[PDB]
Length: 182
Ligand code: HEM
Image 1 (tube, helix red, strand yellow):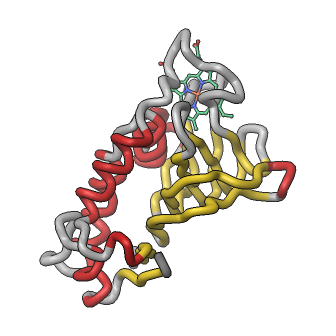
Image 2 (tube, protein in one colour; image 1 turned 180 degrees about the vertical axis):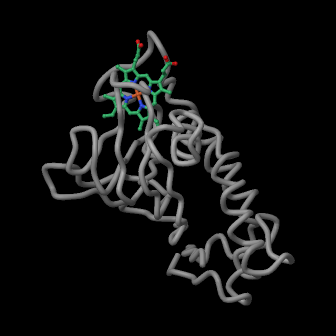
């Protein structure tokens, strides 16, 4: 089942409110045709260059950042082009991205919330319609809607009374979330 980690700072927030606010602040990195600048709005893979166990991206305007973890593959110019696919196990949100391929991995200096055991598996043939792609490209674009939808389904599968409209404290009482120090 989904497992959620959250700083006690967010104990009284709903998941939906936290994610809406986090993504709005992160913003859109404008990873779109004509606007991609390597080292500015591409993010990076570990070990990379275009595959690995992590993909991480910091905002173009502040130190907010996220890390996607799993077994990830990116097609770049190969068909179907510009698709992230593979197995997505986790999304960690916070600020101050540390590490990189030269460090052996990425980590957030201030991890606010993480969602693990996501169990999302997207074949390459689904291209940009795959869930893995939509979740991560959404986050790159400042839009947590796809992530919210996947969390909501995982929470309902535990119990239909649980949803993205539950608070982190409610999800902890329900056995799917645990707090970390502020
Ligand atoms: C090392 C990481 C990455 C690099 C170097 C990279 C590079 C690029 C480049 C060069 C373009 C084309 C810009 C243009 O046509 O002018 C592009 C577009 C795009 N990339 Fe990436 N990308 C990276 C990561 C990702 C990831 C992780 C995703 C998805 C989760 C993604 C999804 C897309 C999409 C959807 C487009 C737009 C394609 C279109 O509308 O034609 N990219 N990227």
